[PDB]
Image (tube, rainbow over all chains, first blue to last red; front, top):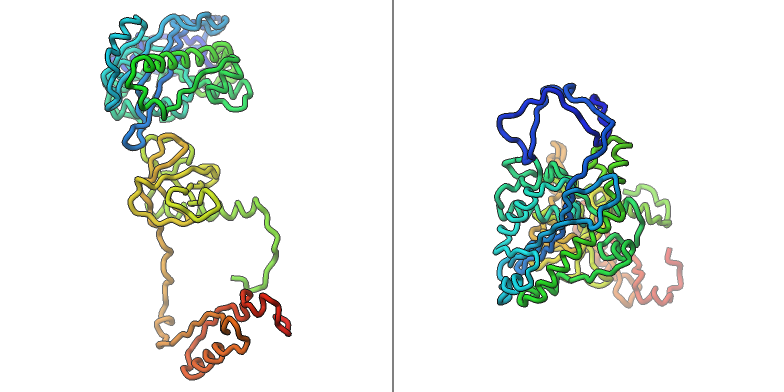
Length: 285
Length: 199
């Protein structure tokens, strides 16, 4: 209120002091003694940002009712316009990874088939290595906006719980700020990065029978996505071909989520709504 | 407790809902304050860590309750009255019946089916605090009997006569007589063979 800041707008800071020790994972840091030292400048256009669309497959543990992440996939777009049309293709790179939770023995010659196909995929020995690789990748890509399905309620919470249980190094890599102690967290979990759930945004924009991913893709993109029941994937891990099929299906799901977000252009809508209202874009999304 | 006769035999579904949710919420507040429970969570919220859940037990179908045909129905202010099946396979010791308010600390990682892990024995109300006058009462004997006071195929009410005889002989202080006094299920009245009005 005091600085008359109305949503995302170019802010110019005078007398930027450089703090001795890093406080975040960002490339540049600055200091401000008083709030009055920073002013608002208007006549500038928004810069392009990085957008990463991610999707993962959890599985209830065989023994007793615990979710376990086994497969991850994510598409990246470094230079994503926020005022122009959604870039086509919506991405220029991606990465996927798979792992055996506790006893799902890898099918014979799995990595051999992977290298034979020469498709973009890496194999992680265990959930801990999977999460470590994911955190390293997200930090190296520093995506400003991370978009997914059911991130608000299911995906983000399970990701955080798995990271905490596995005690993966630098859990704070998810957010741009570095914190030593686990938080316990409505938005503190992803401090610095903009999480966008396609279902809530679609509910905001369009109306559908049910906002589940399959129904949304049907009503929006007029295409059908094959649903893989979680109960059938228990034996899925004993054969390389169908495991690669599952991985490619997760990649397809990530592509569908990204396409829904792009064609529904929820990002520019959020920009304009936040600018009109002046609130925090994260609260808008 | 009904000094007068009554008001109505007309029911309203929203008002019955209000009564039910008020009962659930009152029991819940009492149990929460007694057990120092951190905070309840919505029934449909998928939480990985074990989370205490409040609600009344109910039978899934219209039949007798079975050990794996049980659902939990929450309160409005926490779960909006949603229902969720509960699995008692992991639970060790329990004692449930339909419509009992419980706090269950099971783990629900999917949001569609809870699995119980511990049940909180409900806490009784405090006893009645006496006074000096109450202790100033000598021993008194109480009689209590419950009808019907006539055999299944009689109207002579001989059991009532025997009860009156014992009451006179013992001279008890206070006698409690429960109904029915002319049973509605009695074959004599169920066939409306009586020659006099019920009253």
